Image (tube, rainbow over all chains, first blue to last red; front, side, top):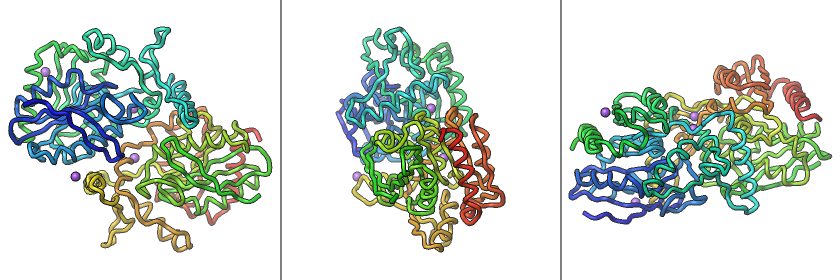
Length: 289
Length: 289
Ligand code: NA
Ligand code: NA
Ligand code: NA
Ligand code: NA
């Protein structure tokens, strides 16, 4: 079946927009969340297509302030709000007659995997959750937290006087990287090298909100919702050690797949059929289909 | 001088309302945050009068969704947002021409002490911070989180359908206390007994937000802002041990004042003059007045 443009409303009044990949008959479903500061457009659509071809209806949408979705400022990341919006997505999805409401899973890549795990921590309507190379910590060096926090205070006060929101680049003109931005600055050239457009700016408030967000503090609440982590062995962008630390904080039932020999992104050039068959088997075993 | 009605706009578009207790000349200032789900009207006004009489201009306002301030749902507690609103309160104090911009301190009681420590962790424009009997953790029995999280999920879906927000009582009809409501159910009869009006309802969304809020994530960032914790020795509502554990997570410069033989709130019948004198001495030493 062809993909559809869809939109749905959040509790806080925003329209989020995305793509629906309907399966050929009523059955399981999957809500897919993209990487850090990225729209739905890159990488995930072909994965959605693969799941759709295996009977899973997929929802792929632009988070708040990204891509085609409402939200101001743009490129202003809020994990707590984004997890909340996944609850609103589940609410929306349940009304689709192709969707068995006991077979709604969440799937997330990179920052989307952080938000996916957090949403699974809170929403027992979710039948299963998969996190692929999740971004666990944005703190960076906490002794360069001070400049960005000062910028965040200046940004508030300036916007209160009608100024535009302040943004940080992934890479300063002097070649520097702002404190919590090395993953972004590392991924951007590889993505753009492959023709994937990248918004190379992020609101300074993004760093403020992440200091109060610690996924390690809520992942113990996912259980008994089955959860799978998919961790590249050689992830230097989202440190493999961080991802395994998160897995260690989770309770059973939880399942781990290590992508042997792969980094944060280059697994897309490996045996992706076998990667997705493994995740499909996880979903089949736990959502029963 | 007489107290004035004041109001100020937050970055996210709300009008918060409060009282101003102006000192007789330009000098230090103090932003005062009340306890859990409580308006500005209780206990704090007389403390503000005392600070005003010692030369400190006080702002005492209703948090979002409380009392005279904007916010929907009502009685929906969001520590992250309330700390953000403390940043906008600092901006309002700085931008108005009554106080010395380098002598703006934060003061908070109970849950207000939590938000005060959080705000001081992020905002280096603050000259000093005082937390009195800060509420550190509202998780309650984590094995009891499920009925509330389910109600939170249901509230979201219902409100999207046009329905009114769902609230919980401090005391259920069978005499039971909802999971994170033991402090509130304990303090309510005592305040009402003294004629202090108590809103005995809390949004089900309050527990949802609080699980992603852990003040111990950020209090190590307060330093170098001088911070003072005032802890009742026999606090059974916010366990003294939680408070001291928070204090040990903080760095220097910090100062601790144990209120010997006092509970969460009954220190208000003791030697408050000497209690406040130790806080005034703390402020004088760090704000040079
Ligand atoms: Na964080
Ligand atoms: Na593997
Ligand atoms: Na509906
Ligand atoms: Na909490």
